[PDB]
Image 1 (cartoon, helix red, strand yellow):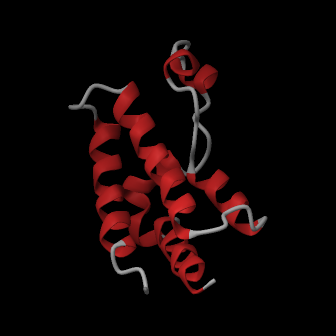
Image 2 (cartoon, rainbow, N blue to C red):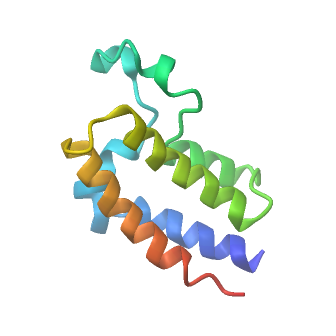
Length: 109
């Protein structure tokens, strides 16, 4: 429970205005059709985004911190897999992942 509160705090931070300039692409599921990404679901087998993480947290789906972290990292990995490494969205992912990893490392234990 204490570790999951730390995870929820991280989640709220990732969704906060402080990080919105680079977090916003990750707020909602990638809408591949809307974006013209007709190969997205052939390349990305397990889509993930912060609204899905939030719903899972609210539903008490995550049983431990590692399960939460695996979903957040999956979200970033999907971005790194789909996009060329010099893409603007990848730069945004890297910045948001830096926020995540440094705070996640402070997990109470």
